[PDB]
Image 1 (cartoon, helix red, strand yellow):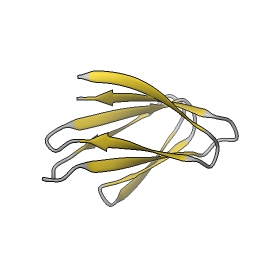
Image 2 (spheres, one colour):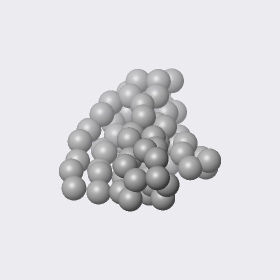
Image 3 (cartoon, one colour):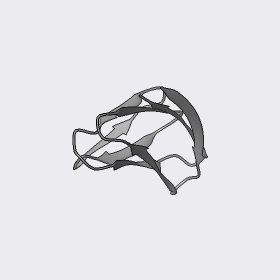
Length: 78
């Protein structure tokens, strides 16, 4: 288990990698949009998005900054 932190500029995107059998969680410091697993989710400030890789293949979760200012994402990997 580990954590890191990334910053995304308005309009820009960032991918979060998850390994098979593992899961991740992203907490958004502001409005954000997520894509993965064929689904989409948007967060309010303070909220977090969870994803679990139930496949045999590596997956990636899309981050998008919906705000007018740079957004911080707290990235947790389990």
